[PDB]
Amino acid sequence: RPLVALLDGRDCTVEMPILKDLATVAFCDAQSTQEIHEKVLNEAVGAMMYHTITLTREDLEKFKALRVIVRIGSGYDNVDIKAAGELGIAVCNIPSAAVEETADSTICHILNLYRRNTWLYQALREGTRVQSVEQIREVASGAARIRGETLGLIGFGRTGQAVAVRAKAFGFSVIFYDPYLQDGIERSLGVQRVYTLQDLLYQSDCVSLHCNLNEHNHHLINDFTIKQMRQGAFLVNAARGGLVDEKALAQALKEGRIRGAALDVHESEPFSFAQGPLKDAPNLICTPHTAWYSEQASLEMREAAATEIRRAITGRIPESLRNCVNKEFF
Amino acid sequence: RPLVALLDGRDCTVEMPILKDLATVAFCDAQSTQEIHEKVLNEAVGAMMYHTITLTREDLEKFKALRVIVRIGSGYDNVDIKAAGELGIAVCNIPSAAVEETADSTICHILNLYRRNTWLYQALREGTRVQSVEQIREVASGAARIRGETLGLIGFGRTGQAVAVRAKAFGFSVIFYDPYLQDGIERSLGVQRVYTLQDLLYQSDCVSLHCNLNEHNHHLINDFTIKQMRQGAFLVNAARGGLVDEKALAQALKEGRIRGAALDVHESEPFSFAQGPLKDAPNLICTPHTAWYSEQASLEMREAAATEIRRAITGRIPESLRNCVNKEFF
Ligand SMILES: NC(=O)c1ccc[n+]([C@@H]2O[C@H](COP(=O)([O-])OP(=O)(O)OC[C@H]3O[C@@H](n4cnc5c(N)ncnc54)[C@H](O)[C@@H]3O)[C@@H](O)[C@H]2O)c1
Ligand SMILES: NC(=O)c1ccc[n+]([C@@H]2O[C@H](COP(=O)([O-])OP(=O)(O)OC[C@H]3O[C@@H](n4cnc5c(N)ncnc54)[C@H](O)[C@@H]3O)[C@@H](O)[C@H]2O)c1
Ligand SMILES: CSCCC(=O)C(=O)O
Ligand SMILES: CSCCC(=O)C(=O)O
């Protein structure tokens, strides 16, 4: 019975029945490879993992039997997939759960910056009394009219498209930058496309990240590129925390160069307001990587992942696999 | 130069230049009829006011010269428009300056409930550490998939229609109840219409109020009608606080019959968490009547109000008036 290990989780209740008849399923609840038991490293043919552990070339080399890794989720930056491919290990993801969950939460972040619902709630919990209209204008200062603003999406894949489709009804003018996309999608969805990041930042009142983290876009948002943004623009990131240099963002918020930011993801997770470069940054929203979460989505993505493993077992790797992201294999 | 009085405001600066050449413009910063100076009562031909003061029949009777009242805002429940009309006073409002602002704020309240953006930010401020995937699901518990949910709007006017239009893209199934509306709109906007409040409540996972407060719908949402709502429904109210019996809502929240509520308006404003019937009610979000507000909207509506006064002075009352809401006039 081939061994399949859930690396950075304990729960295995959705996966059990789907593989029960073909494989031994075990969990390591490891936050690091160091916490992975020797039995697993040596005899595990398949692995399933979330975003909370990282597998480098060195880490991957420790696996003596591993043939397939399945990310429960869409992101796979936390796995060195070229090394994986070179060692004869196939890597897969789940591309289609939490698309709409992430789109909805992202839109929520955007509307939260523009209308200030979260901050106004906070003001009331703090005991602020709002009697006169002048006091209302005062407390809600910065609440902005959305129709006419330009929302610039970096990455126009599944989540970006999902966000655009929702953004239109609020009166956003939607534009995107995605240098790997094929020509035409802009036309299908009736949105405008720009072909440099700079053009995107120059024209945008709100910039929202929806690209996957890769070798070439680490700190995409850095001190230099922030300076390319409109004075008092909004930044939203529900993609990957490595996309943003938080020190730079920290200063921009303080200086008012960015009117506000909403972050679901961070350079170092788990996030804490007492720790890190955003410690004392003003006008900041943070959520602890929950943009994806719903009951159905969590169930759905787990079931799909188990199903990918099942294909990996019964068939040829990587041909039988539905969502393998590393054909720089063998 | 005939006197135009700003009852419950201090700032008078947008309106002055628009009227300087035709009227003396003054402000009272009055919260009640009792603080209004005798000069104004005796000599004001026109009045402009917000929502923070109320004019009863007795109050309107104290005005010896008044010919027009212009509500700076859409709501005019706070003026006895029939009494005004009987005394030969025209009442107008500004019905279209904050429609989209309010729709945007409403949708923001709804998403905050469905995705828990505000509560998750709060959880983080409270120092919750969310490291493991299992822990993420725990903090985001209740976060829901929106596609398939039924959103029921009570009142399908300007804000209601604007809200409908935005809700579609999220996958909400939109249903509405509006017993004063003509037939056909349900078809134009491609949504379902129900013909009793009970049916709307039976079918809605999320109920949102967008009706004007009038003689017949005080405490529309009460102990009785809440029992017509689905177990674990959501309530959002950005219309008027008088629509909801807060005592009733408080118990429903405590008992879980209602999973959560987001309120921009209240029976008694200004709202405080330390005071009133919702004192310690769980799963509550509140904002201090800010749904309408943006710089662009505030300016727009002040200017429109001033222009309405100008028409009242230079033309025929009520014929020259654009948005007179009480042609049960003299
Ligand atoms: N916060 C969350 O919980 C959450 C949930 C889902 C996804 N995500 C993140 O969102 C990312 C995107 O998800 P998706 O399903 O939309 O992925 P996707 O692969 O369908 O789309 C990503 C798009 O970004 C583009 N892109 C890559 N690099 C870019 C760059 N430097 N500039 C501009 N565009 C670039 C790609 O061409 C691609 O079209 C995932 O990688 C994941 O890490 C986060
Ligand atoms: N929070 C804010 O700052 C803010 C901003 C704008 C409006 N409001 C409130 O929201 C209300 C709606 O604004 P609007 O301009 O969209 O109004 P509107 O006149 O365009 O539409 C309101 C609709 O509600 C309907 N209605 C009245 N009584 C009803 C009942 N018992 N059941 C169902 N429907 C009923 C009417 O038929 C009307 O079509 C205003 O009256 C105002 O009091 C609040
Ligand atoms: C690893 S759980 C899913 C969250 C996410 O960001 C993703 O799907 O990539
Ligand atoms: C009186 S300022 C705006 C508040 C409001 O609810 C309205 O538009 O009537």
Image (spheres, coloured by chain):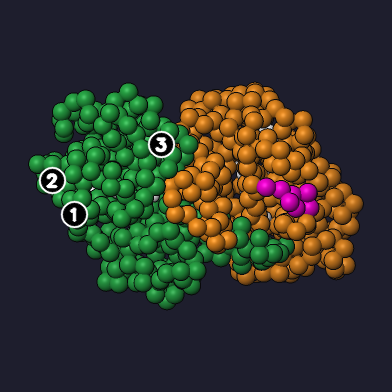
Chain colours: A orange, B green
The mark total stands at 3
Tell me the amino acid under the disc marked 2.
Leu
Chain of the residue where label 3 is placed in the rendered structure: B
Residue B12: which disc? 3
Tags 2 and 1 touching, CB below 8 Å: no
User: Which type of secondary structure does the marked residue at label 3 adopt?
Assistant: loop
Question: Which residue occupies 13% across, 45% down?
Answer: B87
Q: Magenta residues, as a range?
A: A276-282
Is A281 one of the magenta-colored residues?
Answer: yes
Residue found at x 87% / y 49%? A57
Given residues B280 and B9, the one toward you in this image is B9
Q: Nearer the viewer, residue B165 or B53?
A: B53
Chain hosting mark 2: B
The residue at which mark 1 appears reads as B57
How far apart are the alpha carbons under marks 3 and 1?
A: 26 Å
| Res A224 visible | yes
